[PDB]
Image 1 (cartoon, one colour):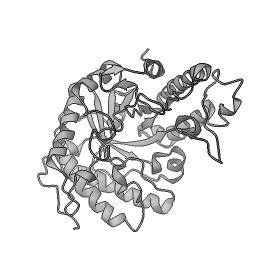
Image 2 (cartoon, rainbow, N blue to C red; image 1 turned 135 degrees about the horizontal axis):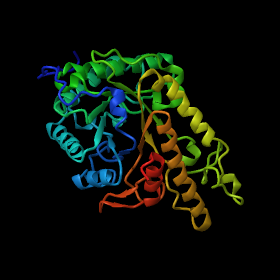
Image 3 (cartoon, helix red, strand yellow; image 1 turned 180 degrees about the vertical axis):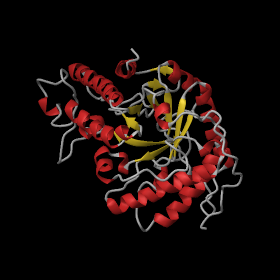
Length: 373
């Protein structure tokens, strides 16, 4: 016992408001939005330039057409490092955000995010024991505090855990089992809450290769899998050229350049997207396990100008429409990664300071891709 038990008020199991299986719950979600660079920000909720989450933001998210939010959350920096006790004020703050999202009729996915790296970069035999202890202590606290929310609230145990081979995958499986066990131990509605488990690095190919089973669960058919998607890197995220490769500015059939053809993709186009999502359809969806596409987005390149900018924005928009549409077609639930930024190399579709739409072109792309428009 490195840390005290935080399973201090375990409750009678309660299935009130928790009647949906994972499959039934997934049917209710076609488009999600990540509250990025906010509650997981190192230094505090506003430390990465976004305002504190407001009811007004969550209202805008719902009214704009999203069914769900994924809320990355930081915890370690709020915790006593001797005892693993999380700040009561921070637990309450998280709870308040969850309540607002539910009040706006959104489904809500809470996680432990990168969180300074304590679990995420340490999927190793050397860290296994101490990290299982922290994973347990944190999840006991988070689940206890958020226990009374109905099925609008889902938990995700980890974010992008860095498991690179079969040995590290067994360590991740331990961490995921510790998560499910901690949640379930708290009882109440947590006996039946749908939980989301992350593939290795949330990478589709590594997950295909390394995944074995879901953690064992006392509940029936209450688990989903999670992967993320930023393929191809050169387009979605790459900010400078390297010896090994160039940034792609352009993407998608119809939106390629005839002049700067070195900025058209050399890989990662439509057929590759289909092939990757097909892997997750076979591995999970076809076995009765929904897949959360927990993050995707291709950043804006507003350092481009004139016709290059115009072309870039067209292919960027189409990329988001295409990923959304092809995900949904294969049982993957697409959650857009929004970092709140409206500047170069950002992904904010809302102006957080004014609760307005900044990037109507991407928003339209997502809604069209979801069949909402």
